[PDB]
Amino acid sequence: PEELQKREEEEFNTGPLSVLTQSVKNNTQVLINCRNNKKLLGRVKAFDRHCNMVLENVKEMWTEVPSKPVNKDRYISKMFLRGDSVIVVLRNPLI
Amino acid sequence: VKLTAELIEQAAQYTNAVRDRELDLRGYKIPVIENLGATLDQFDAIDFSDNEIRKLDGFPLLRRLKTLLVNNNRICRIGEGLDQALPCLTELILTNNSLVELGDLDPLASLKSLTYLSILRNPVTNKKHYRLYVIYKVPQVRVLDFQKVKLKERQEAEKMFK
Amino acid sequence: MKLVRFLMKLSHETVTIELKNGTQVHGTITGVDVSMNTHLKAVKMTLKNREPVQLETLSIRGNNIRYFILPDSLPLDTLL
Amino acid sequence: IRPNHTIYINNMNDKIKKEELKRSLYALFSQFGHVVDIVALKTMKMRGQAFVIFKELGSSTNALRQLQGFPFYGKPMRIQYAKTDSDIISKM
Amino acid sequence: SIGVPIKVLHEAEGHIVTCETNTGEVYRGKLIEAEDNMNCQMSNITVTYRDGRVAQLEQVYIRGSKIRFLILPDMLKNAPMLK
Amino acid sequence: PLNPKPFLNGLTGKPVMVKLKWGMEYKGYLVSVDGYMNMQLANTEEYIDGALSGHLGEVLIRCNNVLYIRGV
Amino acid sequence: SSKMLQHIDYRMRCILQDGRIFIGTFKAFDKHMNLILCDCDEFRKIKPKNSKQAEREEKRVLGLVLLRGENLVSMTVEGPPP
Amino acid sequence: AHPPELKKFMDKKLSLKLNGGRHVQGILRGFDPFMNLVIDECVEMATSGQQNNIGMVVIRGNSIIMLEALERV
Amino acid sequence: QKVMVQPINLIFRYLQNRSRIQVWLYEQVNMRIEGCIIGFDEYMNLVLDDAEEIHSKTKSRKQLGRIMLKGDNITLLQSVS
RNA sequence: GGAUUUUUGGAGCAUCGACCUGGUAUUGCAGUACCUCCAGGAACGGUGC
């Protein structure tokens, strides 16, 4: 109800996902690591309690060995990522 | 009555006694085998008992097929493009045919994965040195007319027609 | 709010669901449930280092899907 | 003896594998009729014996009249009628 | 409630079934008692250990977390629950 | 006795090192720890195989990703 | 909805998590992504491990198979109900 | 949340096989609803011929895949 | 008619006795964390003091200290002392 | 619908199945992991490390 929604808003604003609340406040890009060693950097439009994220204008980079591996990357306009494959989410990336 | 996709779609496809998917098509009297590509490679054995097929040809590319049953027919000639259509063929049942010359089994050696063969009740087996010519033509066949190949038979096949 | 309600309100959209074991199925998603079960029609599936096959219908589970890719002509404000 | 749908075959070679013998029994009985089931047991009580269940008794009668004393795997096999009915024949 | 494959697995008790483990081991035996969480208790089981070495074990119990598949015998194909 | 939830609540601000199941580690000041074992740290350094690799700053690790969390 | 019940009792092929594919008549299903495949056949691809060797797929028929949802990845229709 | 039917394996010497190729043997002293077992006189067998005694071990349900009873049960 | 020994009671007895126990890792038979178990939780998460992770391959034990092992990675906890 | 059994992630060696040669006893009625044993060659293949 309303009290459960207020508790969920308090847990999203003051809990571990508050950095994710930084993704929807100032529209800052976050970097999420996947299970297949593919780091996706992008803004997060929608989130949930199960860490399911909706990314807009994201860039997914990974290492693929053909020797030395190359940094093959791709750019997706809109994407959705489940919380089961999310390993580490960084709020402020380096570059 | 010609064979089409309606006769193959209305046929009974089930599990055979050899734990493989087989479709029964007995009692059809099809003069030519065509339009057999509607199975979408979901069968391993195709039965063609009681048919009036004069030539075993016109088979589509099927990789899941592993057994061919052409028993009780009137096949006088054999096709040449059978190895390119069934690469995983292992069993061939050509019993009760109209093969008279030994040259009809020359495309039958084109199948490299063939191990089982049945040429019983045929006029080609009545001639002399038929099993030796069948062993010298296709050495990959291990069972010919419900009988295993022999080392002395292989030596007699390699010695003859030199 | 949960993200399953935003994914359940999607019909006749050409999406691309990338699975966990190197599989990616691109097709028109026709049905979505609360358990993230994606039922699509006329899809193309490409496995890990394999040829992309084409299937008339597919039903991927929720736990086997790793990521999703939506088209650019899809607003996220009305779906949330 | 009463004609039945299940036909038994004994006096065969038991040195071959069970799958190859089942494939040979399926290939040899495909000309007489539709083979519904092939019971191939290789235990000590029924070694070298097999059974083929047919849909009609006419195909079993033709297989008994045609393959009377047929050479299979270098041995003269004996094809006869079963003393008891089959399971799928009694269930259907 | 109870699922229809769960009811088919519960109705398959007393016959020779074959469970498959997560490590590739296939154990075939007579299912004595089953549970709703795919817990398979089988007697006269034949373990394979993903190498073909089938050893005869007695009173084996495989949990539902590692149970990948459960090959049921063909006698339960005419069950009214599957229709 | 020492339950893990007051141990995680009392470790806020202290520099802890969370080692994941893939061999990597993240050393930083713990900021947020809820009941679902979700960790959120600030000024975190990511290290691989006992050697420091980078500095990620604010980081958030889930429950099924961090293998252990020790004090430093 | 009832999208999973529309493809019931048809010749469907479900892809496993280990890479195998089980093709059979999925007659019964549940909420835990379980499947009851009558006359099922499992096909698993084998690695060539050479330069000139091809990739083969070993197929074995098991009959009625009860597949849990923890191993099933995706299911596709292959053939109509006979 | 139903407990497993581990009443026949109670106070009996069995052998369980954990994940990753691990295997142990001992007497089951209890049962849990989360498939967690307690093994007394636990002897863990590695890939070598030697076996390590543990005394009292507690195995979780997420790692236990199979357990064969070495007794009549 | 028989009594069953619960694993939670054994974990509470090991925490009260302050005995050094070693817990293995899920799908990893090389690394094992050995330490004094201070307490447990409902989700099988343990808190250890002066714990060290020892590898079976390299035969080296690196100290970690007061660690918090989750329940999803715990496989078997054996009492070493 | 997020806490261990299903759905918000543990990510050169051993064994088995075959292929080819000789001696050997069982001729027997049943719904199946696999069924007699010995000796010789192999330049067949899958799985785990």
Image (cartoon, coloured by chain):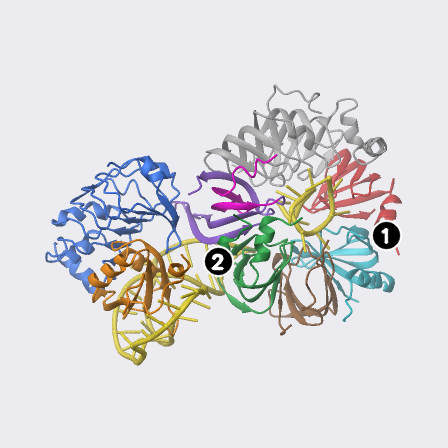
Q: Secondary structure at mark 2?
A: helix
Q: Residue G49 placed where, x, y %?
A: 44, 48
Q: Write down the colour of chain F.
A: red
* Residue F47, quarter of picture: top right
Chain (brown): H
Mark 1, other Cα within 10 Å: few <14 / some 14–19 / many ≥20: some
Q: Residue G56 placed where, x, y %?
A: 41, 47
Q: Write down the colour of chain I.
A: cyan
Q: Write down the colour of chain B.
A: blue
Q: Quadrant of the C terminus of chain B?
A: bottom left
Image label count: 2
Q: Write down the colour of chain J.
A: yellow
Q: Name the residue tied to disc 1.
A: F3
Q: Is residue G15 left or right of residue B135?
A: right
| Residue appearing at x 79%, y 43% in the figure | F36
The reply to whether residue A93 is visible in this rendering is yes
The answer for which chain carries disc 1 is: F
Q: Residue I7 placed where, x, y %?
A: 77, 61
